[PDB]
Image 1 (cartoon, rainbow, N blue to C red):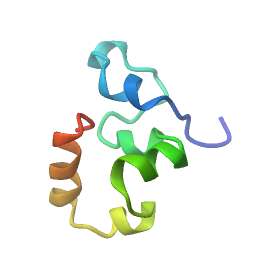
Image 2: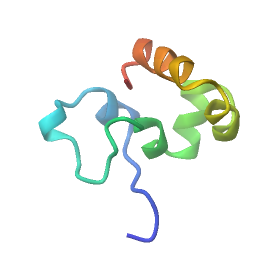
Image 3: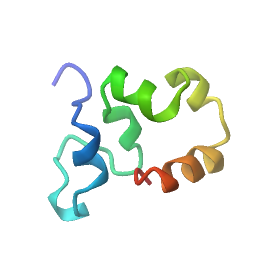
Image 4: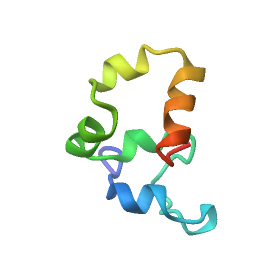
Length: 67
């Protein structure tokens, strides 16, 4: 594609690894949320989230089912 594919939050959270769409980086599911879902889930800009240390990004994602 011309850009990364997006999918509904429920699909990214509640799908077995083997069933995940091919267009989703399993280690960076947040990149595949729409802007609206990213804002609802994280409450900060994508750049602000990317500026958190990787371990903190992961910790936040774990509770949210996106790790």
